[PDB]
Length: 473
Ligand SMILES: [Ca+2]
Ligand SMILES: [Cl-]
Ligand code: NA
Ligand code: NA
Ligand code: NA
Ligand code: NA
Ligand code: NA
Ligand code: NA
Image (cartoon, rainbow, N blue to C red; front, side, top):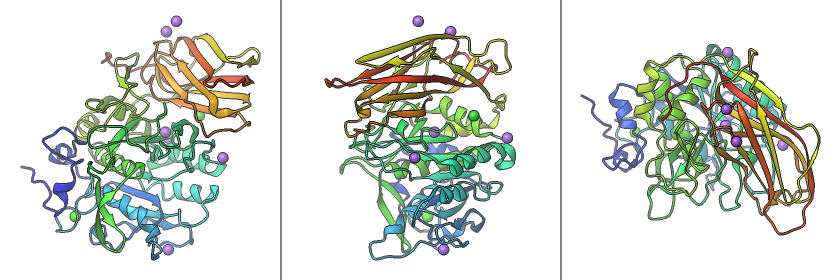
């Protein structure tokens, strides 16, 4: 029968297992025989200490590169401040070696782990693209605990080379099954940022992962948005436990924190899931996450039930990842049908926003055509608008099934007069709904100011299929 790891700090890894039900249910996956064997994960970050006592056994040079210095060796640059400890901490969450008398264990403690040194220098579009596109037929899963600064006032995302890397990855990566891109949703909670204003997390090609504290609350750093898919545990207040992992200079830390710690745990769980079914496509993986993730005991004021009976929150997506449930569902999973894309231009004329604008449109979702969608995956409202103070806007999208997605909440620090230029606000909250019928877009001025602007384009973009639905929850 299964024997849990004996590592010295494993008992402190509260988020991996416990009696309490406040965990990611990882031991249950281990007991089913899945520990990440055969799977390759790469940490895109500031480097990886490849000789660390708890990483060396799992290290994979084929999953590693130094894009900052342009050589194969991803070793972190040592400094007095230990600036470049971040990637090593993330790597240990995924794949720290088990049963070796050192530190704790990775979620997928038998997976192969690499790192791309790419944050320690000027991070250009080209740098991102070379990192995201690294050895895509060897690396299965990419983990990114980085992005635009979450200052609550900018709109930023992948430029051309990085976006091309995402499409090449999901199309041709992993033998055509698609690279798995795991993203940390952000740490701009205190700045009141929205993760839909971040093109990396807002992307359909990335699994954006948010955080919950040990006591099941929304952490101070957490950002709410409709593009988030799911949640893993991370740090909270000083009474709540934190993340245990490998640290720079061959040390062990019990104080890894923030949005940074959530993505790697997700990547580890996804590694166990790929071991259970190597044939899963990038879209299969997101389906599994949607079906198996658990809201229960996560506290939020915005939990809503969507059109197919699933609970969803802007703080948490579909809730906590559940590794046991993921690997169970993966084994006999039937591959989803090819992805369809239904493009619907909503406006006939520009519309003044004023104090409040509501745009109602009944759609057929490409009825009678090859891209007919009856089973929604991602939906985007690609919006082009002008406005005098961007952060005063709040934008909601309501699906025909009555699911209200917040595309954009007020951002008090966003004083931009540049509006949005075909920004593709994305929601995961209507996953598996029938998108036929009335969609409603709401744009409102949340301030008392006399603001002004015009919506000039609203493209509703639907992704999904026309087959294979389950009886709702
Ligand atoms: Ca260990
Ligand atoms: Cl597309
Ligand atoms: Na190097
Ligand atoms: Na940009
Ligand atoms: Na493909
Ligand atoms: Na995403
Ligand atoms: Na309908
Ligand atoms: Na209606």
